[PDB]
Amino acid sequence: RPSGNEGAIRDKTAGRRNNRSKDVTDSATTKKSNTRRATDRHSRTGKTDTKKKVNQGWGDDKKELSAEKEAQADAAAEIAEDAAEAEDA
Amino acid sequence: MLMPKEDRNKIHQYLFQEGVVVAKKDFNQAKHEEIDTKNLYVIKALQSLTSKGYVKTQFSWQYYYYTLTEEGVEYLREYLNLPEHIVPGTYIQERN
Amino acid sequence: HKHKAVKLAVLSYYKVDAEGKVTKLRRECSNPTGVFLANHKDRLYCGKCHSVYKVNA
Amino acid sequence: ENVWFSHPRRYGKGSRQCRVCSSHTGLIRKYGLNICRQCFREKANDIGFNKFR
Amino acid sequence: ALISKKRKLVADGVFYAELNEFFTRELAEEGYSGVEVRVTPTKTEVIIRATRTQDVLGENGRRINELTLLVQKRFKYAPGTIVLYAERVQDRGLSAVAQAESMKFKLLNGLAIRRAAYGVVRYVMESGAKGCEVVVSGKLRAARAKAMKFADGFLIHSGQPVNDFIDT
Amino acid sequence: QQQQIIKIRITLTSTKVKQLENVSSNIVKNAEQHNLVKKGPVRLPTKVLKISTRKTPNGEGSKTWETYEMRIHKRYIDLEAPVQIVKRITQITIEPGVDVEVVVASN
RNA sequence: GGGCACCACCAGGAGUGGAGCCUGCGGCUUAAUUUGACUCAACACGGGGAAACUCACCAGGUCCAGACACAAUAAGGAUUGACAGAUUGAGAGCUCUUUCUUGAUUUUGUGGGUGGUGGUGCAUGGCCGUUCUUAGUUGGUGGAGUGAUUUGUCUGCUUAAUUGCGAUAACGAACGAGACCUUAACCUACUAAAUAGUGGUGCUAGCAUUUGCUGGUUAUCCACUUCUUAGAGGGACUAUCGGUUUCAAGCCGAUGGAAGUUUGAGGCAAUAACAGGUCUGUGAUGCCCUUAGACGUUCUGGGCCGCACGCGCGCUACACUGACGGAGCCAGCGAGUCUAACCUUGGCCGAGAGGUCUUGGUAAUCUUGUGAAACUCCGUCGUGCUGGGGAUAGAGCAUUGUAAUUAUUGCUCUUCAACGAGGAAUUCCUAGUAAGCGCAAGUCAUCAGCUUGCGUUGAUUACGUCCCUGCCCUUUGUACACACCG
Ligand SMILES: [Mg+2]
Ligand SMILES: [Mg+2]
Ligand SMILES: [Mg+2]
Ligand SMILES: [Mg+2]
Ligand SMILES: [Mg+2]
Ligand SMILES: [Mg+2]
Ligand SMILES: [Mg+2]
Ligand SMILES: [Mg+2]
Ligand SMILES: [Mg+2]
Ligand SMILES: [Mg+2]
Ligand SMILES: [Mg+2]
Ligand SMILES: [Mg+2]
Ligand SMILES: [Mg+2]
Ligand SMILES: [Mg+2]
Ligand SMILES: [Mg+2]
Ligand SMILES: [Mg+2]
Ligand SMILES: [Mg+2]
Ligand SMILES: [Mg+2]
Ligand SMILES: [Mg+2]
Ligand SMILES: [Mg+2]
Ligand SMILES: [Mg+2]
Ligand SMILES: [Mg+2]
Ligand SMILES: [Mg+2]
């Protein structure tokens, strides 16, 4: 029972004449439909990351007073040290 | 890292007497520029030097800039039995 | 897989000093390492001059 | 050693690579640049190529 | 060298780009701000603008002979054909690359984002600038990323005056 | 050597027209105060090296293209000039960003 | 309710949807047919034109390129290879027999690294797309409100524009628009040029004549810059004059002008966002997975091209406003090799594709006046699926390549298919524009039916409106705020 490339010419069901008799499956005219972006505003992860996770990771809104009142002085110290190391001493 | 002692000494001698190495990241280049070993051998030996200290490494557009350090300039004298504390190699040797 | 070695002293070349006597034999090849190599069926195969090789065992 | 880079890559996509990142696809080799089109947009002001029109 | 002037000027631009990124990677702690390559006859001069020029020049020829040797070996120049000077940048708080590289090690040393960002925004602003803006984008122990801005003063965003006066 | 005119040509190439014209005016000023005979600064057509890359790193988006471009401005000056004092003034006075090349022509 | 826009319509143009191929997507098939992307904002997109490589996929085969540290170990011993002979792809010592060989470089465990086009782009950076090429955003002081807020930032008119006039509890400002920059258009005004051109002629020289058409030399000529080039400038500001508007911003016409559509075209382009795309651009990257019978890397061969079919971008067509042939004969943007064989003129050979001997060119120098195609003229055809169309298929000759079979592509002869202008629907477009036409560049060893640009020929139709679609603003309602996918 020889098969292979020589068995390809012997093998039935392969060929345009007998593929054209069989009907097209109906999935060929369908669509993938948007990779589940129909409710992308609705978060589907199931985390819904809480108030603490954003008020302690990037901080809350009320801690800006502690940040910039100390960020006033470090740049002034940088100016003082830059005048110290520029050409003085 | 099977690499002969004769080949290893020609990376270490060049690194001592000339200070730095540049090697393109192209393994099987079969010849490093101005080291007469394989480019894979150069990269492979200087990474082995880097891991125990002794060499700093930057990459920067596929070229592996290898620079000898202060612990490495002592290591290249001690284990390799090159003349002791008389040869800086090479940053202040001739040019200053 | 790669290589298994055997405990050895004498490589097919008996003894250079056997109670004051050289007891060497076994017609060699042109290797300066001479050294005595594989023979399957009337066919030696060289070890340093295995690239070009004229007369065998 | 035996067959490690035994295939000829004297030509084609795999002969050349970006000098920044070694990427065979999307490369520009106009004027001997050999930078990919994604790194050329980053470095294009350092090369000297400016958006004018 | 027998190449066309198109390819020669393009390749000199590529050499500038490669040298600039190499010094950006190498001289990060040393306050790098830019490089200028002067191609004189018989030698080329590579001038490094960096705030810590004493850290660039190292300890008595260390760290500047290293960079000269590294550049001449990668670009295959003859020894002595390339010399590599370092002159410090004046008015540090107007170099955007120096301010960004300063913020980078400020945040890598573990300093707060608003503190570092306002500490360079007002440093630029009283270094004598018309305006400054720091945008920080990313995440911090959080599964969601946000970008926050820190602006002070007068800025522009469109036109050739951006190529003129804005340093990014 | 004894003030024999040798017919050099200076080729001036740059991507920066301001500094290139600074060099060109310097050479013409030197050759006019030295009373040299010259064919002056001839300005070649500017080579506009255009690269139309794709603006996106992806495929996604409206298909937007960027025309990055580099201009090469090129000039040449012919100088029938003595050999020593003119090779001195072309050895000195080199601007960065402008590449010079000096070729002696006896054709 | 009012605005705006040929990603809307009107009036039209050119179409597409129908055919055949090309290409991309889905599905099916497969060992694999790698994968991301799905209304605009996926579908000639990932610069994605994949023979190998790329390559991520499949059947197999190597290699370690497993740092470093510790303990064993290798001094008990760790790499290499000549056969031939196989289950071999195989001249792969990959094993296995046989043996020798350079011998603390390794090897084997534990830790820990390193690699990954492996995952998560719903952890991120960066970049890009979109809202939006729209005109929007914000605070100082004052007014209103206990307050969140609101006015300013607006009824009208105008503009391309939160552009301005004007109304006015607001006044005066900033970003965005605009100004800016690049390009195109004018400059017989300036500085010039054997890498551009012209005129005489130092000198020539030819054919026809009574000077027309040319050829050739720049310490083996002179002069000039009109044309060409590129520096610095000039120029336009809707100028002038009418009309009209509240004599306001403006708009319309005419004259002049190189230019009166923001002069044409772009580049840059705010605040706020999107769970938009990308971890498969990177030595951008957290974490996870894998890490030597690997998901690293390499090699061999295949696949990405597989086809009952559905859809999108295109090419070629249905011809006489044309095909064929001969002749005429004209661009512009480019690019190009000694850091090695790139652009190739000329001669010769060849029907052709191509070959071969040389040459110029690292380029305003030479390819190149890219002697391009459409087009024009004269002929053959003659309304016939024809001499339209050129699919499919056969045989042959070449080129590139290590390799062309699943035809790489080119050429010659032959085969000569649907297609007779395309239902429902749908795209783009307002003047050097639509459209026809080729050329250059990109990727490229070879391959353009693609794209980015360039020029050649060059219309019809409106200078408008909210009717459809989308967007913006105001008013209104709200039990929405994860915001109607509520
Ligand atoms: Mg503005
Ligand atoms: Mg603007
Ligand atoms: Mg219509
Ligand atoms: Mg058509
Ligand atoms: Mg069709
Ligand atoms: Mg497929
Ligand atoms: Mg995905
Ligand atoms: Mg892989
Ligand atoms: Mg990676
Ligand atoms: Mg108020
Ligand atoms: Mg308001
Ligand atoms: Mg208003
Ligand atoms: Mg009011
Ligand atoms: Mg002129
Ligand atoms: Mg998503
Ligand atoms: Mg890709
Ligand atoms: Mg393969
Ligand atoms: Mg494909
Ligand atoms: Mg014809
Ligand atoms: Mg022309
Ligand atoms: Mg192909
Ligand atoms: Mg092409
Ligand atoms: Mg394509």
Image (cartoon, rainbow, N blue to C red):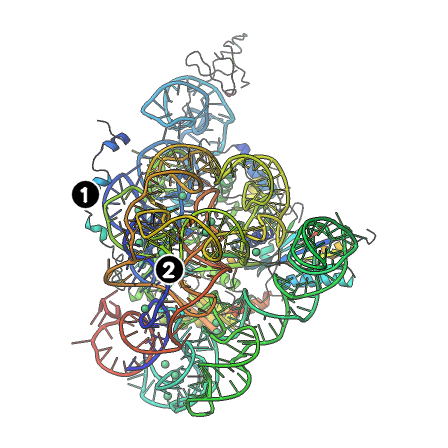
Q: Residue at x 42, y 60 (%)?
A: F64
Q: Within the image, what quadrant is residue F14 found in?
A: bottom right
Q: Within the image, what quadrant is residue A85 found in?
A: bottom right
Residue A64 in the image: state x and y as whole percent.
40, 71
SS for tag 1? Answer: loop
Q: Residue at x 53, y 62 (%)?
A: E98
Q: Is mark 1 within 8 Å of ligand 6?
A: no
Could one spot residue E38 in this view of the protein? yes
Disc number placed over residue F61 in the picture, else none: 2
In the figure, is residue F7 to the left or right of A69? right
SS for tag 2? Answer: loop
Pointer 2 local density, CA inside 10 Å: few below 14, some 14–19, many at least 20? few
In front here: G477 or G335?
G335
Q: Which residue is mark 1?
A: A21
Residue G269 in the image: state x and y as whole percent.
45, 69
User: Closer to us: mark 1 or mark 2?
Assistant: 1
Q: Indicate the chain on which mark 1 is placed.
A: A
In the figure, is residue A59 to the left or right of E77? left
Range of residues picked out in magenta: C41-48
Q: Is residue F8 above or below residue G131?
A: above
In the figure, is residue C52 to the left or right of G159? right
Disc number placed over residue A72 in the picture, else none: none
Q: What amino acid is at disc 2?
A: Gly
Residue G378 in the image: state x and y as whole percent.
48, 53
